[PDB]
Image (cartoon, rainbow over the protein chains, first blue to last red):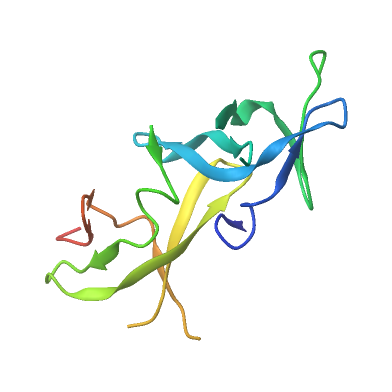
Length: 69
Length: 68
C-alpha cells in the first residue's frame, strides 16, 4: 500500500552495486492487469525504464536486485 | 502500457451520473500484488478514496460506476 505521487516518487533507485540509477519519475502500468510493469526513472538535466521485476526492496530508497538475485 | 502520474493524476473523475467526485491527486498501489488500489481525490485538506475497482474508462476524464 503506497502513495505513488507523495511517496514512491522522487525516490532514488539503486542498482545492486549501490549506485543510483536515478529517481522515480512515473510508473508505467499495464492497462489490462491493472498492474505495475515498470518504473520510469529520471536522469535530471532522459528517462530510464526499469522492469518492476527488478525491484528488490522499497523503503526509503528502492533497491534493484543483482544479476544472480 | 499507461503511464500513471502523467496520464491519470490530475484527471477529474466522474460518477455514473456524470457527476464530478473530484480530481485524482494521487493513486495508491499494493506494492506487493503490483496492483493499483484506489484513486485519492482532492476534495469534492480532505481526501476521498475511490476504489480503483470501479473505473470504467480513462480519457480526458475518468468514468466509473454502473449496474454492477
